[PDB]
Image (cartoon, rainbow, N blue to C red; front, side, top):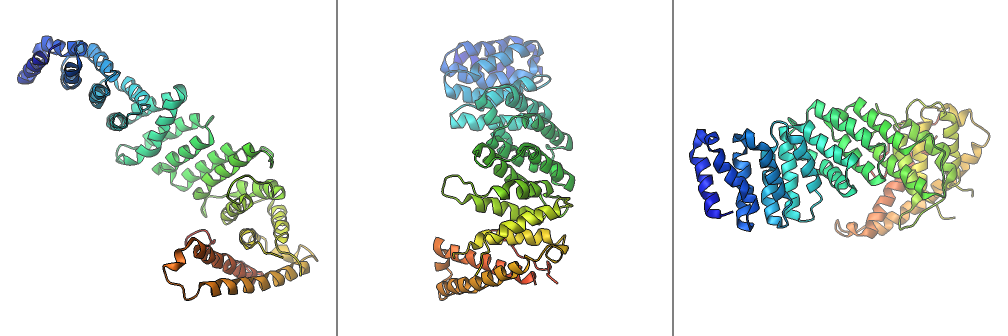
Length: 425
């Protein structure tokens, strides 16, 4: 009720030093503080948490009093109360406290928001599993808004924790819980959840990355057939496949995605969305990237065949040439063909129909390379960064990459290595 009196009782509890428990009466006065007005509540918000640990027989009333302040109409009262919640998260209270803080992430006051995040971090360090239990109960069982905010918390905040806190068991729990959540995630949540998990240190190994790839494969639903018209199919696939790509390496393979693209996607070019990006190219870029991590593929020949066929539609007969498409396709064919140099030799006669397309195409390469190099010379290291000269520079990688790939197909080779034009070394 009165600030004079709250101050005096603070003094009491504070001067009592090691004897504080001998003054349950004073702390009671502090809890009464929550019935007061603004200035009084502002004090109670600091004084209740401060001496909390000294009064077991009053713990229940203490947390409830503090939580009243955490839902005060005055936001600065809420901010002061919320900042101190980690102090209550002792003994068996932390999970209840984790729950409240997660609900509080939905605030739209930015300063409250920051304080809620910091408190979750504090209690996270006190008990990682208990805090995760709170975050994940809300993700699975709470309101959409809270579910969104909690996912963002995990998405942006785990990285700020010391490795010490993020133990093997905590990471195992993050995986286990996310796997329950992943039974039903939008595509945007899927993305967040892939960043969350690919960031776990125990999932950066070969086996960890293998499991991650399998989650993406489960999410994209590869044993489903494929529909070109229906976008609801089209995102799912590309958005999914995009999450897997960073996961591939010599020891972690793209096989199922590659097969699926060959058999189900290629024949179904070209159906497109809007806007103002080129969709068929995006599909091809993806395929080209995964092609160099292809594993032991049963349908190697059939897919290599379907890849080959797709290529010839962009490599005409003796017309505007689609170099960017041909970069992807030739690269993929190059990468898959390596495993089976028996192709081209074994299958057919149509390989003479191929050499002509190459010859022809190559003739268009020199012409285009000439135009690009002519438009680019004399230009300063600064004039090159025009969005126009950027495209031209990239075009030189495209065209020069194709030339190298064609070269190799001379017995035909697969020794050469190109960096895809849109990728760094």
